[PDB]
Amino acid sequence: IKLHTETPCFILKTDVNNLSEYHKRFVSRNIQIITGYIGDTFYFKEFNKEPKRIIKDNWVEF
Amino acid sequence: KDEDIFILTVQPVGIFKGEEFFQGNSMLPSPTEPVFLVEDDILNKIFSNEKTKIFHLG
Amino acid sequence: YGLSLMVVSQRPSEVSDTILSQCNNFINLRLTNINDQNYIKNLLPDNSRSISEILPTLG
């Protein structure tokens, strides 16, 4: 939580509609990720926001 | 008194790069790095030499 | 007269002090005997005592 301060970014050559399925599969396994899409629409601020950390309960946002 | 603190003082003696061992010092793990217990295979890989010069002292 | 010494030893506490004190420059490799390290510290120039603590660590 303290030394790994960078969030990896994975970019797939797919369609936007095929990405909700991956986000669902990640949610079902309790992994927090951010897509940057609210459905066919891309939001600049949501993709490039740094996750918030609480180093007392081992919590990072995504 | 509010909490229980358990502090260990240790001394660097050597570093693992991968599947092998280096001997040295002047190497600093950054704070909050995890600390583990050494497994027996990792220990017995050290203290062992080539079969031509092995003396089992015990 | 054209003669100089470049002394080489592993036990400086055993070599006579009245030649080792004549040495002006030093080539110090790893030393593991405290009785030898203390001698080599006391014999070194003052400007190197602080940097001389590397002898047990040099590899």
Image (spheres, coloured by chain):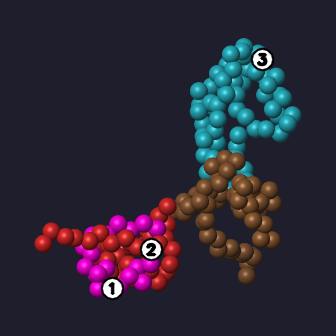
Chain colours: A cyan, B brown, C red
| Residue at far top of view | A15
Q: What number is the disc on residue C17?
A: 1
Residue C25 colored in magenta in the image:
yes
Give percent across and percent down for residue C54: 44, 68
| Residue at far left of view | C1
B20 sits to left or right of A18: left
**Secondary element at tag 3:** helix
Give me the residue at 59% from left, 33% from top: A48
Q: Is residue A45 above or below residue B24?
A: above
Give the quadrant of residue B28.
Answer: bottom right
Give the quadrant of residue C16.
Answer: bottom left
Question: Which kind of residue does numbered mark 2 sit on?
Answer: Gln
Q: Which residues are magenta?
A: C10-30
Mark 3 vs mark 1, foreground winner is 1
Q: Give a yes or no on whether discs 3 and 2 share a subunit.
A: no
- Examine the rendering and report whether any part of residue B29 can be seen: yes
**Secondary element at tag 2:** loop
Q: Nearer the viewer, residue C44 or B49?
A: B49
